[PDB]
Every structure is written in structure tokens, then in C-alpha cells.
Length: 123
Ligand SMILES: [Cl-]
Image 1: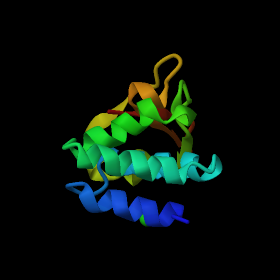
Image 2 (image 1 turned 45 degrees about the horizontal axis):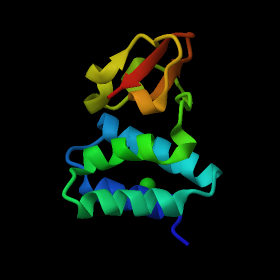
Image 3 (image 1 turned 90 degrees about the vertical axis):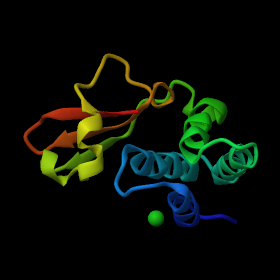
Image 4 (image 1 turned 180 degrees about the vertical axis):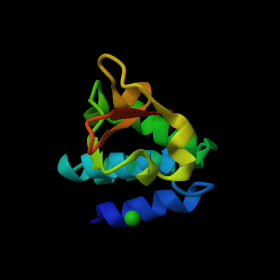
């Protein structure tokens, strides 16, 4: 059976750059997938999108829309010390956290800083 680590690495293989919002989304998708025993469908959806000619970025967003565990799912909250701990390639995708953020609306995660600040990661 495909593991969360296996799948993260497979997805990362197709992504350009390093520590982009799409890299964070891969983490988020694999963790929620793991916890709902859905890694298989997620992998199958990812592969199928690639096979139809979609970009890996599109394939990842399609997962959030087509795999039912992401339906109106709130972004996970990732605790960090400061804004500088968030990778460089994500910094410009950080926003004030909206009302009702959802992963299937492009809110990948919410970072919560030691000092209580919070930032949503938007695609
Ligand atoms: Cl990994």
C-alpha cells in the first residue's frame, strides 16, 4: 500500500521549485488522505489527471475538488515560531485568514505563530 511519504515524494517529483504553496498542499493532501485511508484514491486521481494532460498543479487542485474528504474541509493549522520559518516561495501567498476558509477554495493551511498571529496560505 502506498504510504503518505511515498505519495508526497511522487507528487514533489512533478513540481517545479521548492517550498512553494503547491509543496505545502502536497503535505496537506497526504496528511488528510492518510487520516481518512484515502491515499489510494488520491494517488489514482493524481496519476489520472497527469495522464489526461493536466499540469501537476492542476492535478493537485483537482484532488481538492474531486476527492470527497476535501469537501468544505477547513485548512489544517500549522504551528510555527515566526513568519520567517515559512519557506521563501510561500511568503507572497500568505494572506489574512478569511471567514470560513476551505481547502477546496484554495486555502491550503493556516500558520499560527508563537505570538498568536495567523496567516492563511492561498492558491
Ligand atoms: Cl516527503
